[PDB]
Image (spheres, helix red, strand yellow):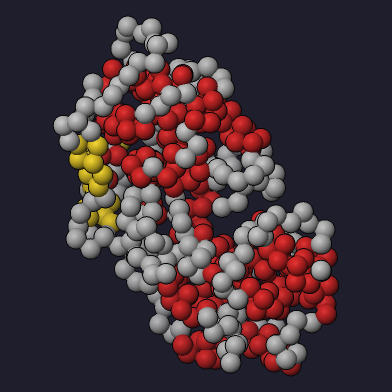
Amino acid sequence: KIFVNPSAIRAGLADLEMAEETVDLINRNIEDNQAHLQGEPIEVDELPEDYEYKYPAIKDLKKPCITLGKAPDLNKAYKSVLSGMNAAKLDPDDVCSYLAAAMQFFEGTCPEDWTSYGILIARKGDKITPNSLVEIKRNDVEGNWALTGGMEMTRDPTVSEHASLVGLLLSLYRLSKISGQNTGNYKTNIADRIEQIFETAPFVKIVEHHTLMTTHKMCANWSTIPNFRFLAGTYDMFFSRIEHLYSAIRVGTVVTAYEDCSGLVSFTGFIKQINLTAREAILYFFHKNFEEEIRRMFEPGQETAVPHSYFIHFRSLGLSGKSPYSSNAVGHVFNLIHFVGCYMGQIRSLNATVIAACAPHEMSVLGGYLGEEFFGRGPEAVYARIMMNGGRLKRSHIRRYVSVSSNHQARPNSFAEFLNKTYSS
């Protein structure tokens, strides 16, 4: 009824495609992103955590698109936006207009043919900028371009200064995205690193230390401004493909990659951790509710295995506002993976948020059995073990869960809290 035999699992999911290539590509990209994310030398695992569905595939050959105001004089826009940065009074519409107008400065050579969802972005050898990836339309409404009052600059900015300002502004996206309680020190260290990056050659110091955090405090929700998020994703896709003098700008935009895909990313990370192929691993997913979710993740046509696809930034680029890859969209898989993580004492899973709707109790049962199996055999053996024990956890599984959760400082709505409430109350 509840659990399904691995034979029936294999039979019912014989139609799956590009599983291994998708897993490998997503995992390699995540590892590469760590250079811009955890590039800071501080890693304290106690740190921030990371209905119908619309698939992102573009079906009409139209590039992702936004609409902004009238193109500005870049020298004046620079002076205005910098004065706003220094005064912690930034106009988001102005900032988006400037970021789009500044895209022309970032030119590189495309190392290979670049096509995604049928859209030919570039041929090998083409000169390319972020504008090549998207359509930025502009109307005739002029921006505000106020000068706060601290701006005493008569000369024109250099391109190096432009690049430093673009980096700082886009870093406000990452700082806004960092949310939750007890994140002050983490954000302060991230901001310090960002300031360092954007005052070090080839960038140039254009603000004093602590300006970025002061401005962030007034821009706390910019990560959900659609045009700003869009521009952050555009810059990130560009620098992900094109090596460039100013690629360190990704320190602020790297968090757009695989945005709203935490279920898929958790799946591929879990597959890598247990050192199995996706085909072999799926057989351990006995529960009847997994099939729908696994098919949801491997829907064809979405380019999950294509390097540098629009897919990697689909959420930031507005290709879909209802991700079929989120933790909620595949809540059973997500809960299972993190109950296994809890069983293995992984702080990241203990602090993850339970998807309450997707049978967390049953998932913790299967999690105990799979955790035992992968702590240090086979799908059929585990299934038989579950049947022999009447679908219940063994006393040893519960002692293990409790020994982990009871000694952990459980956060609200977390897996650790669920485990304490269920097995240690």
Residue 305 visible in image: no
Q: Nearer the viewer, residue 237 or 277?
A: 237
Residue, x 44% and y 50% (percent of image)? 257
Is 252 on the left-hand or right-hand side of 110? right
Is 78 on the left-hand or right-hand side of 374? left
Is 4 on the left-hand or right-hand side of 395? left
Q: Quadrant of the C terminus?
A: bottom right
- 126 above or below 386? above
- 216 above or below 413? above
- Number of residue marks: 0
Residue extending farthest left: 140
Percent of width and height locating residue 222:
44, 39
Percent of width and height locating residue 239:
38, 40
Percent of width and height locating residue 67:
23, 41
- 254 above or below 92? below
- Residue 286, picture quadrant: bottom right
Q: Nearer the viewer, residue 327 or 310?
A: 327
- Residue 403, picture quadrant: bottom right
Residue, x 28% and y 56% (percent of image)? 116
Residue, x 31% and y 45% (percent of image)? 111
Residue, x 20% and y 54% (percent of image)? 62
- 120 above or below 344? above
Q: Quadrant of the N terminus?
A: bottom right
Q: Nearer the viewer, residue 241 or 364?
A: 364
Residue 218 visible in image: yes
Percent of width and height locating residue 369:
71, 79
